[PDB]
Amino acid sequence: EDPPACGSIVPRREWRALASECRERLTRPVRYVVVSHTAGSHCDTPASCAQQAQNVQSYHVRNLGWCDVGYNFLIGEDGLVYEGRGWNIKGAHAGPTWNPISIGISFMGNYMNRVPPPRALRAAQNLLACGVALGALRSNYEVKGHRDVQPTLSPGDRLYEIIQTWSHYRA
Amino acid sequence: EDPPACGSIVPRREWRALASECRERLTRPVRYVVVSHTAGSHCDTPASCAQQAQNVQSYHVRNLGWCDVGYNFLIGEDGLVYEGRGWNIKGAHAGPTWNPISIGISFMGNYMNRVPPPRALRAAQNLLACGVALGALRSNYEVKGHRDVQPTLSPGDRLYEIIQTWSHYRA
Ligand SMILES: CCCCCCCCCCCCCCCC(=O)Oc1ccc([N+](=O)[O-])cc1
């Protein structure tokens, strides 16, 4: 491993994640990033957000039968990025059309009547810049709201409005 | 505005920092990075750590009469980096010898008998990369611990041994 790391990401083990059983890799570089919200409870401390990351992963693995938390990454209102399937593994966030050609990041919480804090927003934007730097993402990658590629309300009305202001957002 | 980002650094305004009156500029790319601990209380949440940066700046400004908090950046156990004097303004952390030829980053707390969490350490190197990425830091920069340049116990026994294993650490 030649390691020149980017950003700060709370690795799987730190948030006590069940080992992954996922195997299908994504093709680098990836062109799309889909932004969703978990629709679950929010957290603003590394302690409560490690917890929530475990909770979301348990729901997906235990109730849905997936190989791993469905998201490649999760964003905490604590301002940290939590590692999901990562940069090289296909997620289960955006359907069978989009899961194979995109990176899915999800903000932990419901943003229909609520906006996430600046640090979460910064954590997300930063991860993406890091994805481009690492070669995992296309320099001209595109960001989509979950609701742009599926019939959901995800990533929440408030959060959707915000990501539409991002330079890489393409409806 | 002012920001399209970087290292997920909490900006001055977000931690409600008094405005700075400092004017001496550092000439990049900067050669050294000095690691210190505040020797103040620690905090592990965005709220408590925003308050703790305010508390440190308050002391430096109102009581020591400094133009702004002396550190270029502060590191909270919440895993975040707090904007201090920044990449361009000379700091007041390591004396007249080192202040003009280095960037000073301080871990908020006393690390003599305590160890800073992995995320705090992550935010630090993540911070230092962001540095190089902007040309704020020297591609091959060197990390020195407070006690390597001044008669002090800073940055603490426990934190000092860790930074001793960093790939850029020097004595
Ligand atoms: C010779 C040893 C190998 C060293 C060469 C490879 C190192 C590449 C390391 C990449 C990881 C750190 C890069 C940080 C990138 C980053 O997020 O900075 C930004 C720079 C600019 C913006 N922006 O949009 O304004 C946002 C972010």
Image: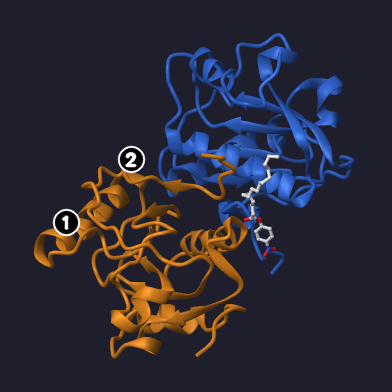
Chain colours: A orange, B blue
* Secondary structure found at label 2: loop
| Residue at 28 percent of width and 49 percent of height | A48
Quadrant including the C terminus of chain B: top right
| Residue at 42 percent of width and 75 percent of height | A101
Which image quarter: residue A57? bottom left
Residue A156 rendering spot, x and y as whole percentages:
35, 80
Is B142 left or right of A89, judged from the image as shown?
right
Discs 2 and 1 lie in a common subunit: yes
Q: Nearer the viewer, residue B162 or A62?
A: A62
| Residue at 45 percent of width and 39 percent of height | B119
Which image quarter: residue A159? bottom left
Residue B59 rendering spot, x and y as whole percentages:
64, 33
Which amino acid lies under the numbered mark 2 shown in the image of this protein?
Glu
Judge whether A75 appears above or below B119 on screen.
below
Q: Which residue is mark 1?
A: A58
Chain at numbered mark 2: A
Q: Which residue is mark 2?
A: A14
Chain at numbered mark 1: A
Q: Nearer the viewer, residue B51 or B114?
A: B114
- Does the rendering let one see residue A114? no
* Secondary structure found at label 1: helix
Which amino acid lies under the numbered mark 1 shown in the image of this protein?
Ser
Query: Within 10 Å of the Cα at label 1, are there few (<14), some (14-19), or many (20+) other Cα atoms?
Result: some
Pointer 2 residue Cβ closer than 8 Å to ligand 1: no
Is B17 left or right of A119, judged from the image as shown?
right
| Residue at 21 percent of width and 59 percent of height | A67
